Amino acid sequence: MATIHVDGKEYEVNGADNLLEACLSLGLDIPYFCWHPALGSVGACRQCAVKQYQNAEDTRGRLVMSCMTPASDGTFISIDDEEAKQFRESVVEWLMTNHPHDCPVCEEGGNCHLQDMTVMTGHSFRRYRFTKRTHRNQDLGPFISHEMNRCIACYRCVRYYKDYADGTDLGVYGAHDNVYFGRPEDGTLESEFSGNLVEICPTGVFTDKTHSERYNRKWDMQFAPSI
Amino acid sequence: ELAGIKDAAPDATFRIRGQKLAREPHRYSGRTAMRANISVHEPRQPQDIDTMFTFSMEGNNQPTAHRSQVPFAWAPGWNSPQAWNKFQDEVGGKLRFGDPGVRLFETSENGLDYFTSVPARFQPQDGKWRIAPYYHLFGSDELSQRAPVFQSRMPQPYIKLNPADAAKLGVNAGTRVSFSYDGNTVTLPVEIAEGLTAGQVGLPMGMSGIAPVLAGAHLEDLKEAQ
Amino acid sequence: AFELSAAEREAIEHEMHHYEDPRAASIEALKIVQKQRGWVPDGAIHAIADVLGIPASDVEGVATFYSQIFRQPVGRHVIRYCDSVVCHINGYQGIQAALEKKLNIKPGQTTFDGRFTLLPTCCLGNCDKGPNMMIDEDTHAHLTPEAIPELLERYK
Amino acid sequence: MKNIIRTPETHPLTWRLRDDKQPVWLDEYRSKNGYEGARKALTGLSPDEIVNQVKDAGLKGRGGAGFSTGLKWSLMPKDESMNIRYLLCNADEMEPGTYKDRLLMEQLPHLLVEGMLISAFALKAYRGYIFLRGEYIEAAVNLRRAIAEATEAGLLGKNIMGTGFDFELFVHTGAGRYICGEETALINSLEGRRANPRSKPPFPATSGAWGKPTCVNNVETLCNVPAILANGVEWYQNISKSKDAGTKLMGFSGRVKNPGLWELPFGTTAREILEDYAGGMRDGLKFKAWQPGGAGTDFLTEAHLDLPMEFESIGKAGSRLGTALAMAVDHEINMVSLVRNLEEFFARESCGWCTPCRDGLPWSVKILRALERGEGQPGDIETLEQLCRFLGPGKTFCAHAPGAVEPLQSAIKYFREEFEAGIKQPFSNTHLINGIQPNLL
Amino acid sequence: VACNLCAVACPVGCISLQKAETKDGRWYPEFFRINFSRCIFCGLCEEACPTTAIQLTPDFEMGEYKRQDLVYEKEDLLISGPGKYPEYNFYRMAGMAIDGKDKGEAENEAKPIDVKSLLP
Ligand SMILES: Cc1cc2nc3c(=O)[nH]c(=O)nc-3n(C[C@H](O)[C@H](O)[C@H](O)COP(=O)(O)O)c2cc1C
Ligand code: SF4
Ligand code: SF4
Ligand code: SF4
Ligand code: SF4
Ligand code: SF4
Ligand code: FES
Ligand code: FES
């Protein structure tokens, strides 16, 4: 349908799709947090940045977001452009400024999308020396435990719970860096599809309480396809 | 009529270019320490004859392996459920080589006739109460209500009455009210349901005591509990 | 045991006529409740939610996003002093030190009496006429620290 | 200077101001050439020719971007079936140093009512909303009383002036957030939602308030059009011999002899504004720097005075014209404190939607506090440079972030001596651990 | 803290453990099992551990009549003091809240600010 040029190479992609699902369909690793195939693109996390040129001869273009840009015919992008790589690493670092020192005691450890994107960008050196912001937690039922310190404000939870699932009792509160995701008051999440948050949230804010009684890491699990 | 089940999954002689399909991640740990408290010798990994899968990590779980039955998603650099993007042809589409499962029956060439069995309108009866089924996600299933984590998630058993039916009966919310089914006697606390139409009695089906066969049945006797 | 009074409801449904959707009136509805009580109590979130026909998490999100909507108990008067850049050039720090010396309560706190709750704020739109403050619905410009006690006297 | 011959020709918006500073109502407003523009518009002109006239006049938005008003009004759809359209007036004015619309709404409310009536007739909008700030109380009383005064003269309501046009005006006050001034976040605030901005495209001209065609315009943009229609477009282009047409409310603020606001045409240089209109700095203080257009604008030096106040003239000078309301910074204000206050404001007013604003700005403010107290570490200046580089246009979700970092990068670029005079301590973010020898760089 | 990193980082797989959690919220191992018949003393477990809980001491004195008695449980491994690093405590760093450590009582952590605070 459409032909795109990525880092000099040429590929065949669907024109209706955006650039993130086009490049992910070709096996090109672009980091992302806020995009989900079911939920769509909103452009919040700014993690999926790629360098876009106007044509083949433009050497200096602009950083765009691949989830928010259509994969039209004639697109010239560079995932591995140095400025794009520096920007994506900087975004990971800005998310890392307030993250708690919890991976040994996090139930998402070994199954955490943030860990994967942090390694994929290659950010391993801390420069931030100041205090970290903290939040108190809420009780969200017998099924889901809550640890708001680990939130990266990707907005996947509210976009899944209100738009997709039409739940009413989960929202975002506050402003600036004090955004709080949860219920107005403690109490069991009433939705019949609340537990998908454990997959939807890319960090360990919403975790399975039934699994945390007898926890083990993902590499120690034995899996089979079942119904 | 069950001829399609051969194509639901391959047989136990199916191999990914000579490899058995793995059940375990390749970095599975502790294989010489799980059973070291019973016997310090290592038992042999169970052999599998039923399925193509092996009860070990010595197998195949490549994203591009020519198969439809994928036990779990993992890719280098993708440890999360987002590794499912590596297993699809396009992201958000279908599995790369097809989703497992086959439909047993196709659409028939010709249809049916019109059913001429039109029911009469519902009429309440004195004495007889129609049982209106109420279903709960956490109560109606036989196996999952025995999960301990649902014991707090299930509500208390309740019998739902129209406000007019509780006004003629003389009861309110919380008044235990005994009834009789099939010569047995069951007592449960009362709840008020405005949307429930009169002549009916709402019961939660599939609970401990209220079988789902009771749908469309009749309660001969209903009286205040003492 | 919170109940929304019938005149707050009459004003909310009066201002609900001016939109396609009642959600658009939610902010104004919250201000009406604050006008009656100084601040928005916790039960007013569910009251507003059930009258407007929107979820309570949307009302609480709106109320927490906007600074002027208060979700914690406030004092009799809300001192709102500007601490923005033009007031930084004109010397608000002396006004802050005078106010917080007199009241003795650092900014964001409440006086033992509760007569005054000191709060900093953004630019009040009166930048050219010097350091500015607002007490309730009254704006005072050309502020000097010496004038602070007498100004306090006005509000007893 | 203190005596100025204010004429209808050179001060079309502000020549109606009385000496006692009290507002002018509809009986006094119509005696001094009031609403004749809206009569000739409703009775004599079609909406499309009015839009073409406003495009030919070359009216630009006074909200701080300077986009052409007639082209934006021509972005509206050409489909009659879409008969539900809205006109929204951005009267928020929460940016520090911006006090211009307060004068227009407190003292000349019928100018705004007439301008929105004309703009609504051009845009075919049946309903108009004035998005007033909720701190401006006397502006809201005077606006609603003047609106209720105009409803009995047949200028609002049903069958206004005999034509079929139906326009209904409303005033709704805000709840006090700066991001509500962004036009898509103004549309979201009007809908009763958290005032996050929206992704562009689509534009509000097609999908705006409640998914209807919408056009958000600054107060002064709407107040300029009655002058255009009453006097004429031919008068309007020939006010100034400059690439920007019409008059602007320009002023100078800070600790100067006469801080204030005066309507002036475009192309006035800073020297007359500062020393002829504002009377210069107070005695015994010398001039260090000036921001041309509020807090979001870049700092400028003494060499950048004597330079015209145009969008493209200030644009090639390294800054942005913004609201055109200037700020004086003198020699006794420490620049680090000024930048720290600015970043405190911008950081604390972030809506929280996008990562590089929500998390970058708190880091920048904490670094600035460390520099101000004198505990700054040697990696701080390159971190501020990196923050300004990666917060530029197109990398964040809206334009609050580039506007937040423009003063920071200009103050580091021109005044690096003060910023680098608070680095008296070396870099250490780790504590020694006994039994583990560290990695020695 | 039963982080299971030592078990996975061991090349021979000689560590088995299960996480437990107190009502206080402190992670601790329900059981810890090291098979010393197979252990080669490579020290990858010590360097994998992010809490310094597991360490290698200068003591080679081992010998047994039965191989079944070479499997060490937690009571054979847990010593009365801190070993090589007397002062490091991991929970002081960690964000998770335990007794004596409410939210904001960690290193380089500010106090929790509620969304309902009057300050904007
Ligand atoms: C953070 C931010 C705040 C803004 N605040 C205002 C404002 O307070 N008043 C205003 O007129 N425009 C403001 N704008 C500009 C508007 O987005 C928009 O460009 C303007 O209202 C267009 O109207 P105009 O054509 O009359 O200038 C702001 C923009 C941003 C990015
Ligand atoms: S949630 Fe993810 S990033 Fe956060 S501590 Fe746990 S594993 Fe690490
Ligand atoms: S709680 Fe989870 S899904 Fe929601 S914003 Fe935080 S990380 Fe994203
Ligand atoms: S860039 Fe900052 S101000 Fe703009 S939408 Fe994102 S978080 Fe809000
Ligand atoms: S603390 Fe050390 S010994 Fe305990 S589980 Fe973690 S890595 Fe293994
Ligand atoms: S020292 Fe022993 S337990 Fe540790 S990694 Fe080596 S073999 Fe495994
Ligand atoms: S995932 Fe694409 S911008 Fe956030
Ligand atoms: S900038 Fe200080 S009150 Fe407006």
Image (tube, rainbow, N blue to C red):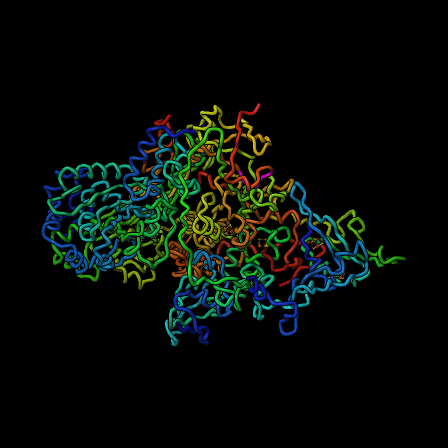
Extreme-right residue of the structure: E65
Q: Nearer the viewer, residue D151 or D68?
A: D151
Eyeballing the image, is B108 above or below C1? below
**Can I make out residue D391 in this image?**
yes
Q: Taken as a whole, is the magenta stretch helix, strand or loop?
A: loop
Give the image location of residue D25, x and y in percent. Answer: 16, 38
**Can I make out residue D274 in this image?**
no
Q: Nearer the viewer, residue D13 or E24?
A: E24
Res C91 → quadrant:
top left
Which segment did they paint magenta? Answer: B204-208
Eyeballing the image, is D418 above or below C122? below
Quadrant of the image where one finds ligand 2:
bottom right
Give the image location of residue D59, x and y in percent. Answer: 21, 57
Q: Nearer the viewer, residue D161 or D217?
A: D161
The residue that appears at 44% across and 54% down in the rendered structure is D354
Give the image location of residue E107, x and y in percent. Answer: 60, 48
Res C40 → quadrant:
top left
Report the side of D217 relative to A25 (left or right): left
Inspect the magenta stretch and tell me whether residue B205 lies in it: yes
Inspect the magenta stretch and tell me whether residue D358 lies in it: no
The residue that appears at 60% across and 58% down in the rendered structure is A226
Count every numbered label the image shows and give the total: 0
Report the side of A109 relative to D128 (left or right): right
Give the image location of residue A180, x and y in percent. Answer: 49, 45
The residue that appears at 44% across and 52% down in the rendered structure is A164
The quarter of the picture where the C terminus of chain E appears is top left
Eyeballing the image, is D422 above or below C8? below
